[PDB]
Amino acid sequence: GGTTNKVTVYYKKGFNSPYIHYRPAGGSWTAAPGVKMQDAEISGYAKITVDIGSASQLEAAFNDGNNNWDSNNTKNYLFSTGTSTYTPGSNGAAGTIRTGAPSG
Image (tube, rainbow, N blue to C red):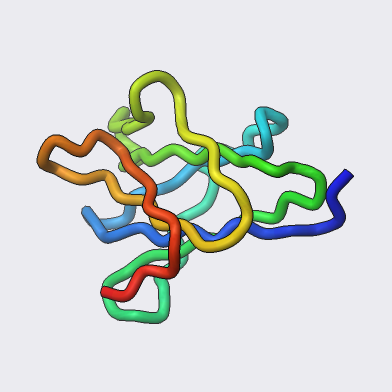
């Protein structure tokens, strides 16, 4: 079903110009690379919105665009509509997403 929802994910930059690739509940894989993280509204942050007028979960991946992919522990993660935050992490955090509107 689903009408027309959207998934907002905030990514913490970063590198230089990394690209993100996501798709609807295992449906179609947008033109790789998906889309270039859209800067947020904070300062130095990134944000992207994906519609899912039928999908309740969408997967997104992170790649520098140079054979530098950063899936997770298999392929990717499942994200739902609302507010989410994508963080690659450096410490003992291998690809993690935190729900809730981020603030700095």
